[PDB]
Length: 214
Length: 217
Image (cartoon, rainbow over all chains, first blue to last red; front, top):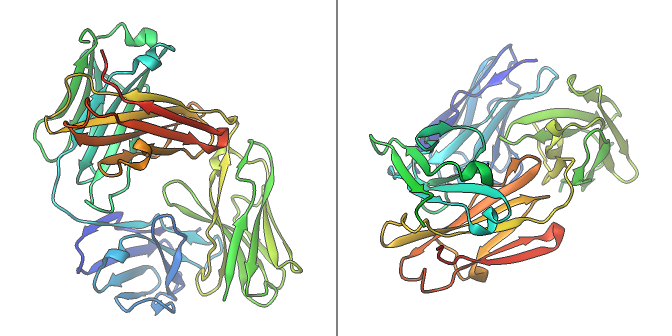
């Protein structure tokens, strides 16, 4: 069916700014493009319908325009409560379809990640498992690449990463990287490195620990 | 005014079939409008599944019209969604909605989890510093909560006493079990000299565990 592409994947802006979100369609959909806003842990809300008609209840700073292919959502003045996910869909052809969504995040000053690594606890080794955990806290922007080196060699198996959404206080992000090994695997190597590389530094941020060190 | 409410099995086994109930209040589903089922995948991606019109018509998304079916009970003012041969690929958030003028009303949506796993309590592991990694003023401690099913898990530090400098990450899948972690950063005054305990609660398995982060050897 007609594919709807949303140009802005994730836009970073300040309170009091003007954004313009893009939504393009494959084929003609005339003006049957609706915009939905979706705050965290909340369902979608109708924002603009008929390409330009503002749904009842929606403030003025929201203004949609466009026809048959190129549509836009203009936000006069961005506000805190406007930080959210925006979806647009067409309702002209019937596989009804939605775009991938554009996320709006609050901009802030760059911050380096506070890296922390932890050897597996004896409570876990004692039962045969080996998890090495690494925390990459309160950094900004999102973009970050973590990497595990065991005794100097990279390792991609048994690495589970998890990222938090932008914080509702300091606007930073955070992630934890967990590496999992059998106790046998664990005890044959000695050096464990968690190497982070963030745009806030020309050199990789590294936390390490040698097993032969109490 | 208009009010939609979903409900249904929260967890099921692959291959199985089921039905999601959307019970709407403050408007007759025979009155007008189309009544839809839309789902959201992990990543916020939205996908339309099907609708049933007030007149009784039914449309389906061609990619699911082999496994789904929409029916209604105009007496109880409800319309249901039936999914068969459910795959893991179907776990998501399911919404029912009224549409026309774009999708006007939406429900709170209901979470479905397609999994073969069986309810099993979490293993909680204390995460104390590697003896060397800790930049003066602040020391970070952690808590590893692995191998548990299903969601969710409640994690707090010092029964609630500690609230800031805290990080709890979204659970992820390892094998077919969830694993999640949490951290707290405290001044290097407290911790060694003051006990910080991590508390984990897995309602499903009626499990409740406290774990003290003590210095390693």
